[PDB]
Image 1 (cartoon, one colour):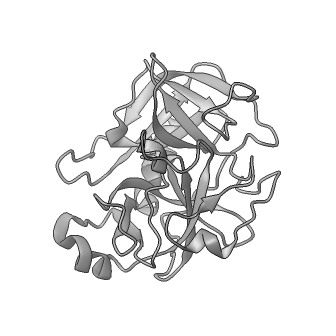
Image 2 (cartoon, rainbow, N blue to C red):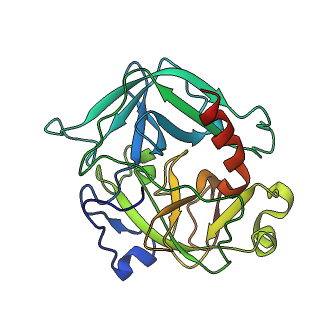
Length: 245
């Protein structure tokens, strides 16, 4: 888990504005959700070859499909895996107004073949403690929501820091709950992360999933932080589900 076959290269440009492109395959547990029509609509993480973490509010259903091993969303050459979901597990506690508890698992039909460019992230322990001020990374094709506005068909990356839930508050007041976690503000956007996209952190040589793109800056401001699923808080769940299925 969390030890890519292709170790990612992160420049400082990763630290400002709208981040920077990623080395292709640099982030393998990274997936995309496409609907029927095939609209890349959400982001996710392989925590295994049978399961996918994701943001609750992505309201994914078995109609959607998981895309894997992608890099540039505008490529047919891709040696990508398109996977079907068997069943879909939204955290029962998922609040829809606050968007607190924003998580949901995807247990696939067929199991995804891992690979160099295909694998999973590591999950924290509830116990884990990613101090505030930690440098993390968010990746995605969020900036692509810019249809006429854009950036890269290609996965971008960004390096932002962990926040105190308090300081975070200084930006979103109460929106911010105990199961959330914010990262950003450091003069670089976060809109590069799709929803359900990952916010991982290193430590002990591994990239561990720390949170999940919940929501952030209407305007992609570089002064506003991002909100994510406080994974630590959401992990037992995971585990539990993971067992019982």
